Image (cartoon, helix red, strand yellow):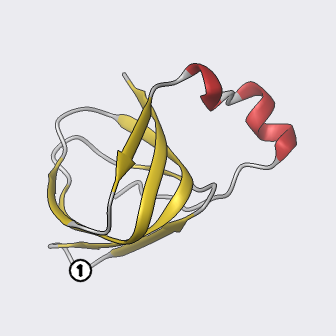
């Protein structure tokens, strides 16, 4: 697995300028996640607790980007209004 948890700082965000990337708005719902491409997303406002079938867990809240491998299948669940940017290949 290649899932990393990091919160880009104003310095790193400059090059990671998510402002140019689309935006997603979501309420504290619950969604099933199935990967299909080396994608990258950045949190801008929200709380999500990810639990993979393999037995892993990715907690990303406010300004946090994580990587995922093609095929990754895990359940997503927002705790508070979620706003994140995208970066898919």
In the picture, the quarter occupied by the N terminus is bottom left
Q: Residue farthest to the right?
A: 11
> Which residue is painted at 20% across and 53% down in the image?
72
| The quarter of the displayed image where residue 77 is located | bottom left
Residue drawn at x 31%, y 69% as measured from the top left = 28
Q: Is residue 32 above or below residue 59?
A: above
Closest to the observer, 23 or 88? 23
* 55 is higher (above) or lower (below) than 45: below
Looking at the rendered structure, the number of numbered marks drawn on it comes to 1
Q: Which residue is mark 1?
A: 55
Q: Which corner quadrant of the image does residue 55 belong to?
A: bottom left
Taking the spot 63% from the left edge, 58% from the top edge, the residue there is 6
> Picture quarter containing residue 29?
bottom left
Q: Residue at x 41, y 54 (%)?
A: 2
Rendering coords of residue 46 (x, y %): 49, 63
Identify the element where label 1 is drawn.
loop
Query: Where is residue 75 shown, x and y percent of the image?
Result: 18, 67
Q: Is residue 34 rendered to the left or right of residue 19?
A: left
> Relative to 13, is 48 on the left or the right?
left
> Would residue 15 appear left or right of 11 to someone viewing this image?
left
Q: Residues within 10 Å of mark 1 (few under 14, many from 20)?
A: few
Q: Quadrant of the C terminus?
A: top left
Residue 86 drawn at (x, y percent): 44, 33
**Above/below status of 25 relative to 31:** above
């Amino acid at each position: 697995m290649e899932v990393k948890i990091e919160k880009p700082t104003p310095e790193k965000l400059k090059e990671l300028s998510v402002e140019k990337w689309p935006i997603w708005e979501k309420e504290v719902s619950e969604f099933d996640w199935y990967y299909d491409t080396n994608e990258t997303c950045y949190i801008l406002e929200g709380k999500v607790e990810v639990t993979t079938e393999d037995g892993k867990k990715y907690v990303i809240e406010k300004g946090d980007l994580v990587t995922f491998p093609k095929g990754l299948r895990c359940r997503w669940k927002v705790l508070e209004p979620v706003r994140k940017h995208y970066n898919l290949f």
